[PDB]
Figure 1 (cartoon, each protein chain N blue to C red):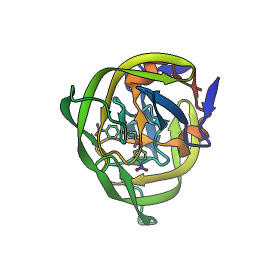
Figure 2: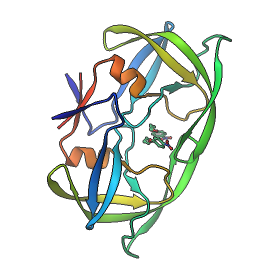
Figure 3: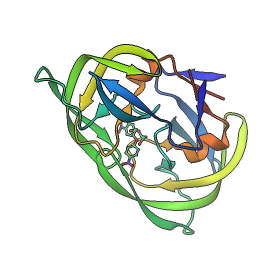
Figure 4: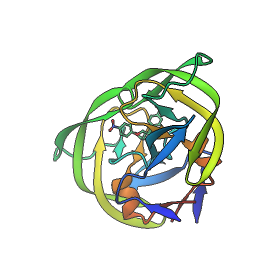
Amino acid sequence: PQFHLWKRPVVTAHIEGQPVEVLLDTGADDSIVTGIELGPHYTPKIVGGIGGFINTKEYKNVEIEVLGKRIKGTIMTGDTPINIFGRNLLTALGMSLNF
Amino acid sequence: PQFHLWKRPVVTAHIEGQPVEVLLDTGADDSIVTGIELGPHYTPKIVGGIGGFINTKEYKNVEIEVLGKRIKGTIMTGDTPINIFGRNLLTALGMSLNF
Ligand SMILES: *[C@@H](CO)COc1ccc([N+](=O)[O-])cc1
Ligand SMILES: *[C@@H](CO)COc1ccc([N+](=O)[O-])cc1
């Protein structure tokens, strides 16, 4: 199945049972979500994007249900204006960019 | 043909004959390049990303050669740390996200 990119490619994902609307982004190496609570077992990171960088909390082996599959992967939480699933997860889901 | 996302999906594009290395990004609505010179016929814009927003120069109907096709589309130039082709162009190229 595939997303045609006329509209933003957005899905609903369950991260540790919490539902979140995420943008699937081939231009992110990482995934970063906000408004989810995931533990005190994190390592601090800073990731950069267009306007500069942000502080994040890297959480490993989180549980994620999306597109009828349950995968485990690294998620960061931080003050992103949009939740994205980077390439770290898109590869876990077998996604390719096709033309 | 398709990109498998184990590596960043990067191509070389010719924009008004200038070669530029670009990241194909399904999470960008817009394309923004730096280090290219494109005219004084632009409209000012500001686009936001992760660390905040940036000032851009929107140029319309620019000439772009990429993946064996010559398309025309809107390109912005501004101080991006990475050059990306947003969804405005990926649709011009018939790209879908497949799984
Ligand atoms: C597309 C979605 O906004 C942009 O992706 C990136 C911007 C900046 C960087 N970086 O500075 O490393 C990577 C990806
Ligand atoms: C993925 C590549 O870095 C991120 O894409 C976006 C970040 C932020 C926004 N926004 O604030 O509208 C859009 C896309």
